[PDB]
């Protein structure tokens, strides 16, 4: 998961 | 270096060190090196899914004198030697050049930043  | 903003979908650790493995089939799905190499799976991910390794590489510029073409290791040796006690603020090139990294990591102790956040 990448939140940026 | 840490993958800032990235969390492993199997073990839930975040901002992890090492290589990052991104699934190219599942949406927004990443695994840390440990979960990848051990064949961990969660939700709709399978070990047959192609994955992209995201990580290191790069030549870097010294922020104090402007010389170019360092590796991460050679940058640290250059800085810890010729720019040992300099208190001038600079932006970390390693952080800025790496995917998801901090584009403006301002520091007034680059040598210490390298030793703590960019361990070899
Ligand atoms: Zn993991
Ligand atoms: Zn997948
Ligand atoms: Zn320099
Ligand atoms: Zn940095």
Image (tube, rainbow, N blue to C red):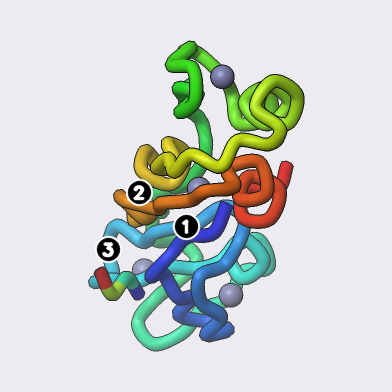
Who's the residue at 52% across and 48% down the image? Answer: B108
Marks 3/1: CA–CA distance: 12 Å
Pick whichever of labels 1 and 2 is earlier in the sequence.
1
What residue does disc 3 label? B25
Cβ–Cβ below 8 Å for labels 3 and 2? Answer: no
Count all numbered tags in the image, as a single digit: 3
Q: Specify few, some or many for label 2: CA neighbours under 10 Å numbering under 14, 14-19, or 20 or more.
A: some
Q: Please determine if labels 1 and 2 lie on a single subunit.
A: yes
What residue does disc 1 label? B21
Q: Is residue A3 above or below residue B2?
A: below
Who's the residue at 54% across and 59% down the image? Answer: B2
- Please state if B118 lies on the left or on the right of A4 as rendered: right
Q: Nearer the viewer, residue B69 or B91?
A: B91
Cβ of mark 3 under 8 A from ligand 2: yes
What residue does disc 2 label? B99
Q: Which label sits in the foreground, 3 or 1?
A: 1
Who's the residue at 43% across and 64% down the image? Answer: B4
Q: Specify few, some or many for label 1: CA neighbours under 10 Å numbering under 14, 14-19, or 20 or more.
A: many
Marks 3/2: CA–CA distance: 19 Å
């Amino acid at each position: 998961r990448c939140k940026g | 270096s840490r993958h800032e903003g990235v969390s492993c979908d199997a073990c839930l650790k975040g901002n992890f060190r090492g290589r990052r493995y991104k699934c190219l089939i599942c949406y927004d799905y990443d695994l840390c090196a440990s979960c990848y190499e051990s064949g961990a799976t969660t939700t709709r991910h399978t070990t047959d899914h192609p994955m992209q390794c995201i990580g290191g590489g790069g030549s870097f510029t010294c922020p104090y004198c402007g010389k170019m073409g360092y590796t991460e290791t050679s940058l640290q040796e250059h800085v810890t030697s010729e720019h040992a006690e300099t208190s001038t603020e600079v932006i970390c090139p390693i952080c800025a050049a790496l995917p998801g990294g901090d584009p403006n990591h301002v520091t007034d102790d680059f040598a210490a930043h390298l030793t703590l956040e960019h361990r070899a």
